[PDB]
Amino acid sequence: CRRWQWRMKKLGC
Image (cartoon, rainbow, N blue to C red; front, side, top):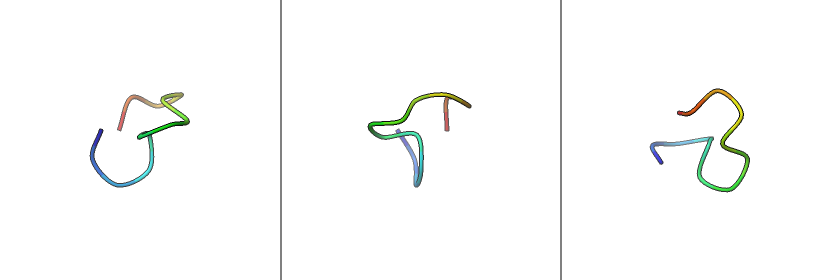
């Protein structure tokens, strides 16, 4: 998604 919420899209990157 950006640099964190790629798999763990909790914050939505």
